[PDB]
Length: 142
Image (cartoon, rainbow, N blue to C red; front, side, top):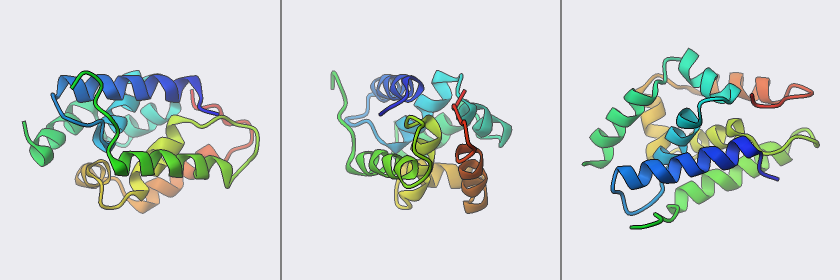
C-alpha cells in the first residue's frame, strides 16, 4: 500500500531521470524524487542532514555522467522491494512512505543512490535514526 507521498516522489523521480536524459530511473532519481516532492518528513530529514537537492544532482552528474518513460534499474526495483519490507517487517497500519524508500536505497549498498548519500555524509547511524522516526506509533511521513 504505497502512500500518496511515495507515489508523488516516484513521479518526481521519473521526471528527473527524463530531465537528465538517462535511459533508466535509478536509485539516484528515486532519491531526488523524494527531495523534489518536498513535503514529506523524509525530505525535511534529508535537508536537515545537509543532503540538499542541488548537491545530489551535482553528485549524480559526477558519478553517472552528463526514452519517453525511463524504466527502473534493477537496484531501484530492489530498493522499492526493501521499502515494502521495512514497512512490512515493522508496525502494521501505515502505508509505504518516502522514509521506507530512502531506507531501501541506503540498503542497496552498490547503488548510485547509496554512494551519493555516502558522499554527502549519510551513514548507517542516520539510517537507524530515520528508522526510529518511521517506527513511531502513528507515523505519517509528512
